[PDB]
Image 1 (cartoon, chains in turn red, yellow):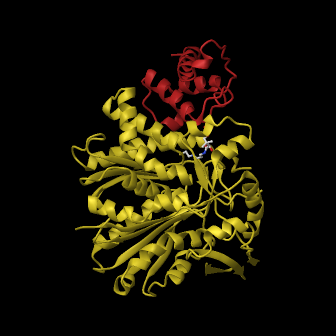
Image 2 (tube, chains in turn cyan, green):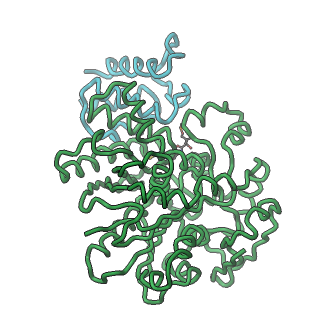
Image 3 (cartoon, rainbow over the protein chains, first blue to last red):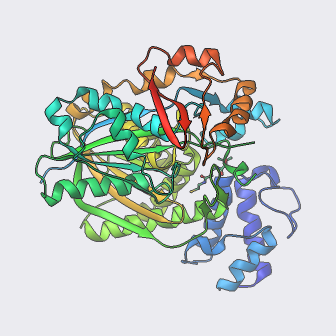
Length: 79
Length: 410
Ligand SMILES: *P(=O)(O)OCC(C)(C)[C@@H](O)C(=O)NCCC(=O)NCCS
């Protein structure tokens, strides 16, 4: 799977977690924090994407991204 | 061999701030902190410190003991990330003001919020060693959040003050330990740290992911050692290190999804039954660092059902990091003893700070910063707060004189 395919999956669970963003355009430079997604739900999105991709590695390996585009890059690098 | 907690006592501070007031003061909707299951945080006054918190937590334990039983306390472990000296343990002051024996090992233990659990495990092993049959240990987890007016801004809403004292012995009237039922897991990570005094630094997002990793792996280690254990069926209640309740709800959900393949409604019902009772007191004090899991245990006992004996699973995490999953049993008799401590009443009687008082408190806190050589406290900083403390047999910090801390019963 590629960077762009993963970004779509991140957008899906983001909208699933924050229904108010269902009809909102999300850019790669958008940050979950600035979108209003709280601390627990930012972790939840990561774990949902990990599970969707069957990526069974430590959760901390997906830390440190400053926007969803960078999160996509992190996932892409792991497989 | 029987071992565990003979007595448990809590000090949840003299004053608290309602987080709705903080939200209002920073233009946030109320729903942000209610969403995260946060209600109030305890706040240390300038005339309190981790020693005074510790002594206030332990005093009810010592007051109940016979002279003979008080003299049997031969180890005092203070568990803290709020230390007052690079070498002097807070245990020395604690021993002095509680009137304990001079034939007593005394030291302080550090590993962020894992400190309390580490101390409890060392105390358990003293009893199990049978090196000194009849000896007891006193383990006190004590921490304050003395923010000065930042690296710490991420933690303001969540960072409380509190202490929990445990008497550990071969007659565990409150919590009977499942001996050798332990899993533990740790590794070096820069999730949060305290590289300067009176402060905290880190990436809370990384810290949450690390907590979740440890929750899984520490429990797996326990499961490997305790054949046939089931995360739903073996534990009547679950108590967790609780930085804030919302993330414990998330951790429990993650564990239930992976271990039991449970559906969302089932998980939420299980959360309310097994996890919410432990959150009740945590919501009233905030994160009290190494003491928080012990407060959660006390909350589980008071707020859950012990009409028959119950097994409680315990998860400890400390940033940096290390973690442990362990367990024990509480009987109806133990729960009845615990109820006599009146924790809920104690917490309800604290002074409720205005946002104006809270801001003044932060400003005034610099006078007792780490490294202070001389200070003489004004007890009448807030006359109304004092009226709540005076006459209750509380220890306070009176002064520091050439680095020597002086305390007073008021
Ligand atoms: P999030 O942006 O919803 O923030 C959560 C919160 C406002 C409680 C915040 O103050 C915070 O992150 N505090 C907790 C810091 C901490 O101790 N994290 C530990 C995670 S194991």
